[PDB]
Every structure is written in C-alpha cells, then in structure tokens.
Amino acid sequence: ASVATAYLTLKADQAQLQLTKDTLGTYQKSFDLTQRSYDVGVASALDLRQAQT
Amino acid sequence: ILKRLFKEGSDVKAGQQLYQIDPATYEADYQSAQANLASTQEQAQRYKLLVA
C-alpha cells in the first residue's frame, strides 16, 4: 500500500510540474507583453512591476 | 481688418493675400485642435507599434 501510494504521488507530481511549467510560460509571455508595452509608452511602470512580481 | 497687402488697382494673382482679418479667435481653436491631434497621433502610433 505504501509503495503504491508513493508511486501515485510521484505520478501526480510529474503532471503538477508539467502544468507549473506551462503557467510559468503564460506568466513569462504576459511579462514580455507588458515589457513591450512599457518600452513604447502605453503602460506605466506600475503595471510592469505588477506583471513582474 | 488689421492690414491690407495689395496696391490698389494692381493685377493680383489667384491665391495672393489681400487682407488680414483678425486671427485672435481662430488661432485659439486652431491650437486647441492641434493639441488634440498631438495627443491622438502619439496614441495611434503607440498602438500601431503594440499591435505588431
């Protein structure tokens, strides 16, 4: 029972890491768009910091 | 009238300035519309760079 539930936790956390990498990709592309909007002049630096955090 | 800029009885060219009627209440809303254009032009160019 213990080795079955240990393999099930590892199997779930592989997919947890796979989803967290995709969330990091979405946040990183949102920061890239806010950096482009800051570099031209539309967005202020406050939205740039709020996208960086 | 502020001045006239032709000799009377002279052959005038199509487009030559004749008089000078007071540009006191028209330079005001000319620079008003010019300021509105100076805002919206560098709104549209910023959005043209961001849509790319």
Image (cartoon, rainbow, N blue to C red):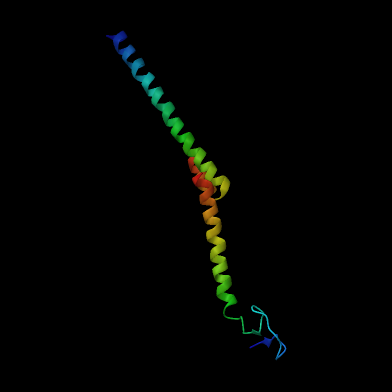
Q: Position of residue B33 (x, y in %)?
A: 54, 69
Q: x and y percent of residue A52 in the render?
A: 51, 39
Q: Is residue A43 visible?
A: no
Residue A36's place in the image compared with B22, above or below, is: above
Q: Is residue A16 above or below residue B14?
A: above
The correct choice, above or below, for B22 with respect to A44 in the image is: below
- Horizontal side, residue B10 vs residue A12: left or right: right
Rendered view: A43 above or below A2: below
On-image quarter of the N terminus of chain B: bottom right
- Identify which residue is drawn at 46% across, 31% down: A25
Relative side of B23 to A11, left or right = right
Residue that extends furthest to the left in the rendered view of this protein = A1
Residue at image position (57%, 73%) is B30
- State left or right for residue B27 relative to residue A19: right
Any part of residue A50 in sight:
yes
Question: Toward the viewer: B36 or B2?
Answer: B2
Please give the name of the residue rendered at 27% of the width and 9% of the height, measured from the top-left corner: A1
- The one nearer the camera, A44 or B44, is B44
Count of numbered tags: 0
Is residue A15 left or right of B36 when viewed as pictured?
Answer: left
Q: Where is residue A3 shown, x and y percent of the image?
A: 31, 8
Q: Position of residue B51 (x, y in %)?
A: 49, 46
* Quadrant housing residue B6: bottom right
Which residue sits furthest front?
Answer: B11
